[PDB]
Length: 133
Ligand SMILES: CCCCCCCCCCCCCCCC(=O)O
Image (cartoon, rainbow, N blue to C red; front, side, top):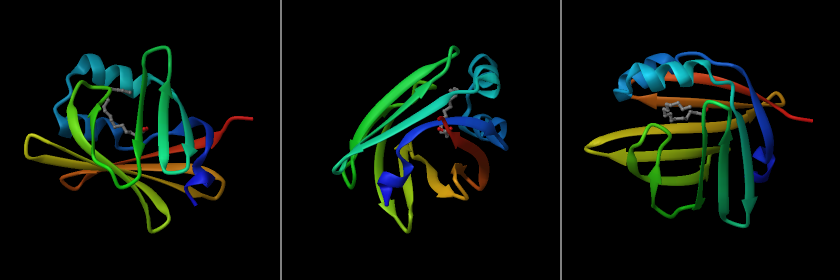
């Protein structure tokens, strides 16, 4: 259940994230910030409404969405995208679309921690998050 993803999570490990950002076309300024920020990810749900808030000194982002409904997302790197979030096959899937390109971030609960995987054109990433308190 999506509720099982609720809570404040802290990043304990990252992998492939720098390759992904490169794949998107993000420059060093943001690539360095992302590569060195150890953000907190707060996920809360209300029925079908869902909010994902990212917090760090180097950056703070946040967006809300209703499962199954498309919406305009202003990504941390400045992209406006047509995002849809849908909880399917036991994971939260955040599919993005912009300028003919696509990308999807998948968040799932595993062994007690939140495992976030991002993919774009076969280039992927894997961030592990442990619940705070
Ligand atoms: C932290 C911001 C760094 C700037 C680069 C942002 C690149 C956009 C990344 C968007 C995808 C983020 C999803 C990664 C998964 C996660 O939430 O940790």
